[PDB]
Amino acid sequence: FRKMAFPSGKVEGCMVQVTCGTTTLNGLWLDDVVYCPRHVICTSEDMLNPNYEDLLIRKSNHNFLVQAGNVQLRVIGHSMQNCVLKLRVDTANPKTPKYKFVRIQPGQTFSVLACYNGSPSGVYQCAMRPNFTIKGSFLNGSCGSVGFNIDYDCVSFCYMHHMELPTGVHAGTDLEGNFYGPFVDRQTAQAAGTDTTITVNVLAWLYAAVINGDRWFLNRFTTTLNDFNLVAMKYNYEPLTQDHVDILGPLSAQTGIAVLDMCASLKELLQNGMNGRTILGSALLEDEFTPFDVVRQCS
Amino acid sequence: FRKMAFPSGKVEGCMVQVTCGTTTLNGLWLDDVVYCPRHVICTSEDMLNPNYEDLLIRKSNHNFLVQAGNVQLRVIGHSMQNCVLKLRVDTANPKTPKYKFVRIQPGQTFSVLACYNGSPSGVYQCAMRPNFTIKGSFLNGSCGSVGFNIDYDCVSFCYMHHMELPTGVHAGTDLEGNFYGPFVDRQTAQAAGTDTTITVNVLAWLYAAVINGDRWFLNRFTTTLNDFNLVAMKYNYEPLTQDHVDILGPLSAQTGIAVLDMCASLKELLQNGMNGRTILGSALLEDEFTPFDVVRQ
Ligand SMILES: Cn1cnc(Cn2c(=O)nc(Nc3cc4cn(C)nc4cc3Cl)n(Cc3cc(F)c(F)cc3F)c2=O)n1
Ligand SMILES: Cn1cnc(Cn2c(=O)nc(Nc3cc4cn(C)nc4cc3Cl)n(Cc3cc(F)c(F)cc3F)c2=O)n1
């Protein structure tokens, strides 16, 4: 049982480089439009406190250099949608997959294709944190890298990377240009709200552990949904809804362990700790696998 | 630090399905050859103790169903090299990347493109364990999935998945069909040897911690390589090779910490533990990041 990302080929064929003067980052080329963070129009000076409508009115199509590998794509139009710039180009991307733009909710996972200067570099799985950050692996030049899910050859794009916060976590937008979380696309120090643990995901991962043979944390105690949620809230865990209980149904059926019985196991782990033991080789309770992630990798 | 895979697109374009009768698995289509585990020629009654030479003689080109998606690739020649079947097909794959076949050492990492029925499903990073297994994530139908590294647009293929062992770890071959480890391609219970910790990779992880400013474990001692190797084996750690010392060179240079001084720091951690302290936010020493992985990040 590993963190597993979707195959990245359908997205690799869409990555391009976008340059404005000295400023360069990654863009996403779908049909005849390139999507990228609007931060690209900023000079070093502009970055600290940009007025984007002002900066963009002073721009012309020919100010934008879009490179797909070695081939330059000519910009024939541009517009801004919130924090995303849309560059219309005179060529359609022949590698454009079937795709959709989606806004995900906290706790949901996605694959990240980290890119630098328009070239893909690596792929890994992430989760939208409850405080709307992501704990990614991004370096300088990764701005504009995207996160996505794939279902039946349709790529659902959900994240476009913008910035690293002082704590090392990451902030970005959906592909409509709206930030996840209370952040803005300005180079100034920004903190996130206090984060919490994604409870339904921890439970899914405990089920993964049982499916893979690690059972030491199970017990014969039990709990009600409300009494579990009281303890969860005490420990900065997200509440578990009846919808979450329903979504864990397939894993409870496969393992014969009722959801509220797994909740009682988690309650004990929160109250007692792991006593130096590990679960799926982890010394800490992992919360970045969804119930669907576990079902897909174990079935 | 987390495990990151290489982008998988160059390998996705090479995955195909190979079927013999009802036995079906994944193959790798490069130029006009498809590579796949020879186990595919086993009927369910042959899988226990197959006579592969006798099974191959009964086979003709037209017995092999090779499919890219739903498109059949006509087989024009077939041969067996060690544990891999090589099916020559009448179409050169237009998506063939620049590639080579390499045989890796324990501790080396690679990306796995897990596939089912010729269809890529997921990608993740893996390390070759000292006992020549990999702690992968594979289901039924994954036979023939490959592992690879990418360096400057060249794909180095290093693993072809064959089987799951009773302990849940996985065993396979290089792309010349030679198994990693003392395994054979028969559906018989084979136990993996006792595993050990990948010392060169733990050392890389310590350098990564130093680079990020976490350096409490740097002690005032040094050691010789022979001295360290003898101590390491008493803690179930792998001995270091001359090649290992060399691949730590870049990280040693970047930090200014001699390899042998870092060995002495590791030795102290093996003989005393960590005393509640963590390294890179982890109470456990990570051994599946190579020195290349560390610099890669
Ligand atoms: C360490 N790290 C992790 N993720 C990131 C992402 N990231 C980034 O790749 N680039 C940024 N600033 C730029 C500087 C440039 C210098 N040149 C020549 N061109 C540049 C282009 C960019 Cl985008 N930033 C900072 C940043 C990016 C934003 F989109 C934003 F709204 C505010 C910010 F402070 C950055 O975080 N780096
Ligand atoms: C749970 N798991 C994790 N990895 C694996 C890999 N694996 C596999 O995918 N298939 C195997 N046997 C087959 C059965 C088939 C049934 N049909 C209809 N077609 C089949 C094709 C195969 Cl390959 N095996 C077992 C196995 C495969 C070998 F290549 C080998 F040499 C020995 C073995 F015991 C398998 O491990 N499953």
Image (cartoon, coloured by chain):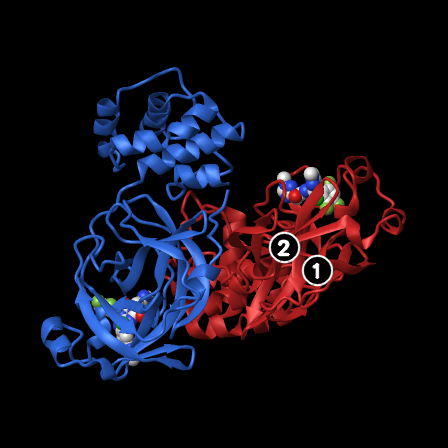
Chain colours: A red, B blue
In the rendered structure, the answer to whether residue A146 lies left or right of residue A299 reads right
| Mark 1 lies on residue | A34
Secondary-structure class at tag 1: strand
Quarter residue A78 falls in: bottom right
Q: Nearer the viewer, residue A228 or A27?
A: A27
Q: Do residues under tags 2 and 1 come within 8 Å of each other at their CB atoms?
A: yes
- The quarter holding residue B175 reads bottom left
Examine the rendering and report whether any part of residue B168 can be seen: no
**Residue at the image point whose x is 79% and y is 43% from the top:** A42
Q: Residues within 10 Å of mark 2 (few under 14, many from 20)?
A: many
Amino acid type of the residue tagged 2 in the rendering = Val
* Residue extending farthest top: B220
Is ligand 1 within 8 Å of the beta carbon of the residue shown at mark 2? no
Task: Report the chain holding disc 1.
Answer: A
Question: Picture coordinates of residue B140 (x, y %)?
Answer: 34, 71
The residue at 40%/63% (across/down) is B96
Decide if residue B160 is on the left or right side of residue A242. left
* Subunit ID for the residue under disc 2: A
Question: How far from the left and from the top, in percent, is residue A63?
Answer: 78, 49
Q: Nearer the viewer, residue A147 or B234?
A: A147
**For the residues marked 2 and 1, what is the alpha-carbon distance in whole angstroms?**
8 Å
Q: Amino acid at mark 1?
A: Val
Q: Give the percent coordinates (x, y) of residue B103.
A: 27, 50
Label 2, on which residue?
A: A16
